[PDB]
Length: 83
Ligand SMILES: CN[C@@H](C)C(=O)N[C@@H]1C(=O)N(Cc2c(OC)ccc3cc(C(=O)O)ccc23)c2ccccc2OC12CCOCC2
Ligand SMILES: [Zn+2]
Image (cartoon, rainbow, N blue to C red; front, side):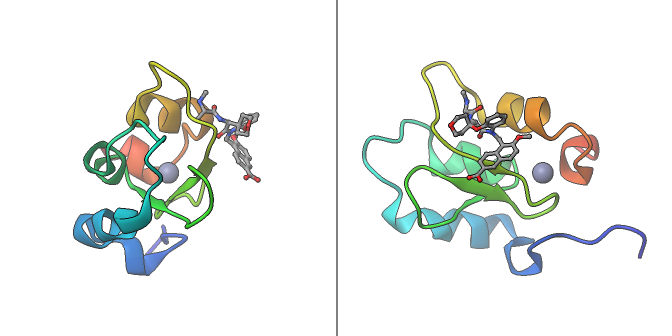
């Protein structure tokens, strides 16, 4: 087709949810919320990445939401625009 996910293996929400097995205990956003916004854990710090656009998000701050940070930084993501 005309679009293509950066990371096809993380197409699935369940696969993204599994990536957070070792999400650090200081990272306040839940794997549920992050996976639901297309994000999976890169294994490094609190850095997640979008399966669709490939955008990365890290150094999360209080009051950050997954979807709002995803949209803010990566507004042309097909996942963000398809939601
Ligand atoms: C406050 N909410 C958090 C999620 C946030 O916005 N984090 C940014 C954040 O996640 N981004 C997104 C982002 C980008 O947004 C367009 C672009 C490239 C990025 C590259 C890396 C990386 O090499 O690891 C990480 C993030 C990138 C960001 C955007 C613009 C300037 C700096 C950015 O980096 C930080 C802010 C400083 O520490 C590194 C992460
Ligand atoms: Zn995205």
